[PDB]
Image (tube, rainbow over all chains, first blue to last red; front, side, top):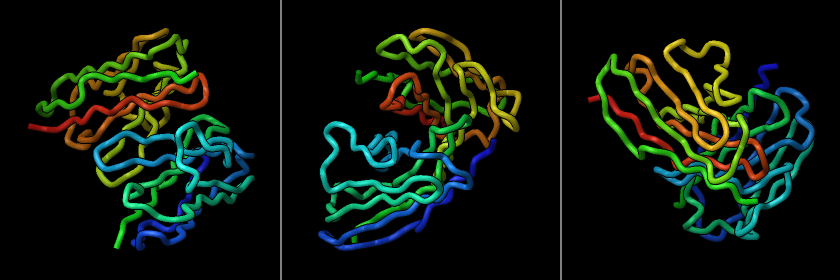
Amino acid sequence: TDIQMTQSPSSLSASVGDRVTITCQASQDISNYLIWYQQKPGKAPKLLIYDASNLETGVPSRFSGSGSGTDFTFTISSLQPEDIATYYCQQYHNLPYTFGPGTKLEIK
Amino acid sequence: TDIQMTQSPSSLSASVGDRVTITCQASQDISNYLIWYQQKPGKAPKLLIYDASNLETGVPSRFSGSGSGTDFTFTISSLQPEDIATYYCQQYHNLPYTFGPGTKLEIK
């Protein structure tokens, strides 16, 4: 039914080159039907990861995703200036498809 | 493969109580696998319409969606202040699940 997607942290600031680790928790088992989107300010979300851990074409290798079941992790190995954005997870296991509340990542 | 989602208009301003009609064209036939989301400023997208024309529960009746194939329409029958948001279409016919580029709706 109404699957609730939780996401932590809500916001964070870091330096160029740091490792960033973001979580997304589902309120019910969603198997590996988890997407991660990047939404730069004023733009649409851009799919980065599907099936929990698969990167789409053209996505820089610094992005990775992991998890399965109810707990998921998105990692940026080396934060870059172009990564300033809000990141969202989304499950596509069951309609309606639901979003986490976002993680706003900034530099400094 | 890479389905392109086009959305028009890019931005628009209107008054409280007006009818608003926004369109979304897909670059390939997606049957009726089209979602419409509402994203209020600072928040995550929230699903309003699925299967091109089906409204989710709790969605105000002023919202509607239509279309099938390659052309889709989202309509607000009577614009309200709480409707200031960016609206996005999204296809879920084939991964990756591509987004429209957004329609920014403002009052005044």
